[PDB]
Each structure stands twice: as C-alpha cells, then as structure tokens.
Image 1: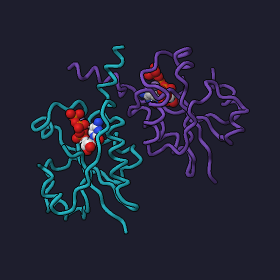
Image 2: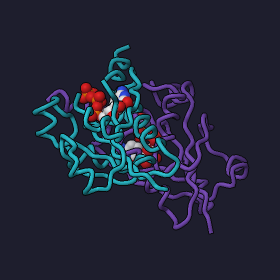
Image 3: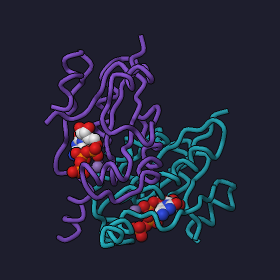
Length: 129
Length: 129
Ligand SMILES: Nc1ccn([C@@H]2O[C@@H](COP(=O)(O)OP(=O)(O)OP(=O)(O)O)[C@@H](O)[C@H]2O)c(=O)n1
Ligand SMILES: Nc1ccn([C@@H]2O[C@@H](COP(=O)(O)OP(=O)(O)OP(=O)(O)O)[C@@H](O)[C@H]2O)c(=O)n1
Ligand SMILES: [Mn+2]
Ligand SMILES: [Mn+2]
C-alpha cells in the first residue's frame, strides 16, 4: 500500500515553492514515504551554479519540513536505475521543464508544479520596496 | 498526558533559528500539541518593526513545519490569562531576553534558546561574499 517517492534538488535557501513541491510529492498517493535527495556543493556549482548554503545547512533545514520522511544527503546528481533499486524508490518527483525521459518511459516520473514569484531572492527584492 | 505549548512570534522570513525554536517548544514534554501564534502586520510594525512577509505569507510557511500542530493567525500581541484559558494552553515558549514575568510567576513559561547567525538576512550577507 505504501509508495516510496523520491524528490531531488538543491533546495538552497528553502522557500514556499520548495515546500509546496515537497507537499505535492508527499501527496502523490494516499500512503507514501517521501525521500529527499540534496545535491552536493561541488556538483551543483559544477552543473547548476553557486549555492548559497552548504550541503550541511541545506540538509538541516529540510529536516524540519513536515512532508519529508527521509533524506539522502548528498545525493547523486543523475538518478540511475541501480539507485532506484537500492532505495526501493517507486516514483521520482521533480518539476518538468530530457533528463527524465527514461523515468517517464518506465512509468516512474511524477511531475510537480513550480510556484513562481515566491523565491527567497524575490523576497530580498521586496525588501527593496 | 498531553501538554499544550504555545509559541508566539513574527516568524518573518522563516529560517533555521525559528525552526529550531519550534522544535524546542514541541519537545518541551513527551506528548505535546504545539500551537503557534503569528503576529499581525500592523501590530508588529507598530511595536517591533517592518515585516517583510504578510501575515498570510508568514502563516502559510509555518504550515509546512513538522513541529507545528496548530496555528493562531493572527494572534494577540500580548498573551493574557483569558487567552490561555480559551485555548487550554499549559505553557508559553519564547526566548527570554519583563513581559513574561506573570507567566513565570504562574509556572507557565518555558524559555527557549535563540540560535544566532542563522537568520535569512545573515544569508544575504553571505551572498555578498
Ligand atoms: N519556485 C519553485 C522552486 C522549486 N520548485 C521545485 O523544487 C525543485 C527542486 O529543487 P532545486 O533543485 O532547488 O530547484 P530551483 O529552485 O528550480 O533552482 P535555482 O537554483 O535556479 O533557484 C523542483 O522539484 C521543482 O518542482 C518549485 O516547485 N517551485
Ligand atoms: N535566531 C532566532 C530567531 C528567533 N528565535 C525564536 O523565535 C522567536 C519568535 O519569533 P520572532 O517573533 O520572529 O522573533 P526575532 O526573529 O527574534 O526578531 P527580528 O524581527 O529582529 O528578526 C522567539 O521565540 C525566539 O526564541 C530563535 O530562537 N533564534
Ligand atoms: Mn534551490
Ligand atoms: Mn521574525
């Protein structure tokens, strides 16, 4: 009955958008375990960009989120089939903007919706009045 | 067996310090209900200072925190004995830096520890390298 969901990301400076994505993930099915993978500092910087918070900081904040059942920190950048088997993961949840083609082909991808305009750094903009 | 804890604050731009305080509050006793009160925009500005996020935003973020069982939003600025009776509150938890004298006299105050240097706006400083 219980379904293992895996959501990965940077989760830098956690904001409402991240938290809403985690809720979506958690709620994909009636009974779930939500595993969150947090990407490493150097892989993020290498492939995505400067991260503000360290892995240790980004991971500690996620510990406090209601939807998060388990954390894999650091997590591998690219998910692989072996990785899915190691953690008995049933679905991978992430926004969908193809690195996730093979998961969609397998029926293992559950797209989640971004919520724009609610990023921490949008808030700094508001501080600027 | 179950103990009602009440923690109030602004909780603007929620960060690790807030989340650690909420965990402390929640963990004051073995079995607790943690109620969080979020202060109104105009009372905060009037007594404390400019708030970045609205009451509606500050409250929505708290919804996602694992330790939070119930939210009172907005909450009264000053807690009163009548208020404690309305919500069957057993203890009030807040940092202790006296507005809480009457609660200490009653045995109803549980001080919590700030964690400094982990505020969102300290993070903007780090962005400045
Ligand atoms: N405003 C946002 C930001 C993120 N997410 C979700 O969180 C992402 C994973 O986290 P991250 O790797 O942190 O992504 P971004 O925040 O998209 O990236 P940037 O560094 O450019 O802010 C994806 O699952 C996406 O669905 C979201 O739903 N809404
Ligand atoms: N770094 C912090 C910030 C807040 N808190 C806790 O959260 C506070 C309640 O929230 P708020 O009213 O938001 O307080 P400050 O964050 O202290 O205020 P400022 O607006 O000056 O940042 C108190 O309970 C305090 O113990 C904490 O423990 N550590
Ligand atoms: Mn991020
Ligand atoms: Mn605050």
